[PDB]
View (tube, rainbow, N blue to C red):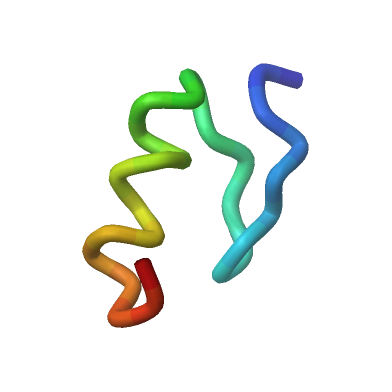
Length: 28
């Protein structure tokens, strides 16, 4: 509902975290 960006496999609550995920995803 919040963020459909299922990057590794999770719906994010805000863009900030979905943005702080790629930072801690070894991809940036």
